[PDB]
Image: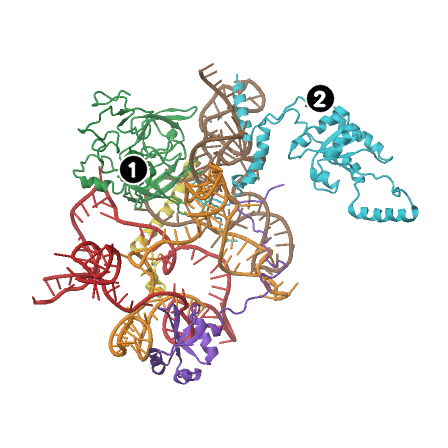
Chain colours: A cyan, B yellow, C purple, D green, E orange, F red, G brown
Amino acid sequence: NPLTHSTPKNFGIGQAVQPKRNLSRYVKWPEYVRVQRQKKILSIRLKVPPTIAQFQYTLDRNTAAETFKLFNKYRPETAAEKKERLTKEAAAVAEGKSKQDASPKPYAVKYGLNHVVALIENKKAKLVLIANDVDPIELVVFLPALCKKMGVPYAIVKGKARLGTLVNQKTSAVAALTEVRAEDEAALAKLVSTIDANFADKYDEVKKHWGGGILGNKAQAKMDKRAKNSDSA
Amino acid sequence: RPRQYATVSKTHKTVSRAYGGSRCANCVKERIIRAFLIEEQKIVKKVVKEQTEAAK
Amino acid sequence: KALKVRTSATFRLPKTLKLARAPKYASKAVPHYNRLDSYKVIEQPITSETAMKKVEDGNILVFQVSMKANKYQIKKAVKELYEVDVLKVNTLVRPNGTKKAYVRLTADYDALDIANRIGYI
Amino acid sequence: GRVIRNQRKGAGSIFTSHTRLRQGAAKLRTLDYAERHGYIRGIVKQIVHDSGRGAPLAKVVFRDPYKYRLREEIFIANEGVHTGQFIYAGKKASLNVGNVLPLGSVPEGTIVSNVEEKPGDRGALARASGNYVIIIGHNPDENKTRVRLPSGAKKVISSDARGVIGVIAGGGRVDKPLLKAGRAFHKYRLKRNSWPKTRGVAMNPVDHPHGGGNHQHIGKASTISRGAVSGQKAGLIAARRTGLLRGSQKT
RNA sequence: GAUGGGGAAGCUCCGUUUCAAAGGCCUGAUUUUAUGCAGGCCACCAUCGAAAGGGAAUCCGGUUAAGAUUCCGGAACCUGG
RNA sequence: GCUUGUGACGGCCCGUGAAAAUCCACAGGAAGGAAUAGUUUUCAUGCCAGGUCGUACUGAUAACCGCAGCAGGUCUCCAAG
RNA sequence: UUUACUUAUUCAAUGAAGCGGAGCUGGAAUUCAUUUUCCACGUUCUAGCAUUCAAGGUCCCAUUCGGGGCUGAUCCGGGUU
């Protein structure tokens, strides 16, 4: 009790060599870190065209899981099960003599940008899931455009890695259904209606809206000072 | 010679006093004097300036 | 959530797990035999008149050794071949591009009775 | 012809600088954080001669504000600075010779030397012996400072540029005639090899524009244009007038 | 004079700390034990470049046809372990 | 007295007359420690090893360079009455 | 012709350390209810010293030999300036 004293040091300008702090702001990251950080900085200081800014607007958290409970039931068949059906299907050929019609219709989530574009052109789609994270954006900029002109409802949803595991891949960049079991139209119908009010119905407004253009904290604060100073009268 | 200060015992390379083998006898005395007077002057400035602010 | 605390203004390369090599097969499938043997370090003696005078006088053995040898190999080789102890080794590359060794035995051994044991005297 | 002596200087083969005994890069202290809001006290350890220049240099020692370290600075000594002095470097540092203060935070009419002309250069104009700067007038908004250079030039630089108050030591170094060729030999043994100088008129036409002819003469005008090329620019570059300086500066 | 890079059709030129994630030492922990794992410290920075610069330490006597501060006898010192 | 080393000074400079490896010291208090016993290898003594290449000779009115055994050229140390 | 912005491009600095905004305490202001500010908000007789995740306060642990969290040292924005 009495042997311990109280030092407290004075960390100001001239004494008390400074304490260790968090200089995470003051770290010179590798060039690859800076280029990707300034990749999105530069993309929001520029006037992004109006055919884009359809993206950066995504199905919300509440309706993400509900949209993804339906797609997750109809997961495309894995390799292990596919090995099981074929040896069963071949066996059914041996004595059942069925014309490769042993198993019923497959129900799985469709995908593939060359596949889905054909499905959209043939009116064989009723809900399209689209990832917003395509590094080449030109692969999808027409996908919201095809869906409206044909009349298909689409949902630009966050994440390829999450559209990937739905397909048992790493990325899919697209996902859809074209024919569903008789017990899921009740879930599908109202799910389609929700995305209409977000992506389909609002499309003819977003066709004329630009994005980005936002400034940095030090520059947004500057106009705040400039406007309020000039606001005095 | 500088390399030969490795094979020589410790009593040949330093003197007993603080800062022994490095500083002068009178220079060590000088910083002994200087340290005391202004570590006592600081606690004089410390009490003097707290009196001026306390009056106001 | 909150990030990790980084007290430095620098960021360095993290230490990764560096595995070893044992790829699939040997580099040469036969390790080489001993290149510099005890029989290759020492070729032959010098029996010149100057060299022979050294033998009886200074308990020194004069040998013609490999150009690739050093004094550790010469000391070990003399011990193996002749069962004698070397006190010191002196080397000189002769003006004909060959190495000569002055091998001095301990007082336990006499080079006179060893030189004729080899067969030169 | 042949390329001429002022053309051969840019190859930098034998016309480099002699830098074996030059002490270091005599710069100012860095503007990290402890001067822009406060100050930091420093000590002068020794003032030494610099080979190549005629102004002494000071060894100013500061404590590291971020490590248990004693980082030392190489300043150009102000006339009046002495070993053992205390040096204050900051924004609120007093107006005393030896202190390092910004131009925007010193009163008009101040004598300052070793003055940056962009904040953070660690040293710029008024470096030579007996040279200084004076502040003429501040422009507080869009912060600027109006100062006069040793050449007599008025230059506006950022208000937060720095400078040591006072004048460089060693003034009047040139009032003494060298009296001797070999005295100029030692002045330029440690500066550079720009001495001695054969005249260009005492040359051969292959070696110089001015060479040749039965008498030693220029032949054409020695006043040369700006647009002249390397090889033609020997003489009085870009001269507006010439002759003998009659009148004032008329600037 | 490499490197990271930047030019140059190109043989090659610039440039030596430069718009590099650039490197390694002490002590622990287990004594299935290799060093994974406890940790902290370090920010300079390839290398080559002087038998007259800098630099750890050997002296005397004797000895050969021809070698010796190197052999022999004696007497030392230095570095590393 | 000659030659050479060394010391304390003086004159001189708009000339003020290298760099690193390496070696030591100091400040600081991490840790480790004592009683039937601990600690220091900056004290002394005692043990082992010290690799590679060079080393002969001339060094010049004959061994180098000058077509050569050339009145030329070629850096330096010691210096008796 | 003048003029405005920052992310492109151009220039300079540091091991990219204290940038921007706001907030806790106020020397000097008229508040005409309820606060608007320049900004104040650890160092200047003196050639000493300032380093060990910082001592202190506090909450836990499984006591120990000590260990950890917060604060001491305002928060937010990741724009190095």
Q: Residues within 10 Å of mark 1 (few under 14, many from 20)?
A: many
Farthest-out residue, right: A96
- Report the Cα–Cα distance between label 1 and label 2: 74 Å
Res. D226 in view? yes
Q: Residues within 10 Å of mark 2 (few under 14, many from 20)?
A: few
Q: Amino acid at mark 1?
A: Asn
Circle 1 or circle 2, nearest the eye: 2
Farthest-out residue, bottom: C113
Which chain's residue wears label 1? Answer: D
Residue G53: percent from left, percent from top: 51, 49
Closest to the observer: C19 or D94? Answer: C19
Which chain's residue wears label 2? Answer: A
Q: Secondary structure at mark 2?
A: helix
User: Is the same chain shared between marks 1 and 2?
Assistant: no
Q: Quadrant of the C terminus of chain D?
A: top left
Image disc number at residue A171: none
Name the residue rendered at 72%, 28% in the picture. A144
Name the residue rendered at 61%, 59% in the picture. C22
Which residue is labeled 2 in the image?
A: A204
Name the residue rendered at 65%, 24% in the picture. A50
Residue A24: percent from left, percent from top: 54, 41
Q: Secondary structure at mark 1?
A: loop
Against F81, is C61 above or below? below
Which residue is labeled 1 in the image?
A: D78
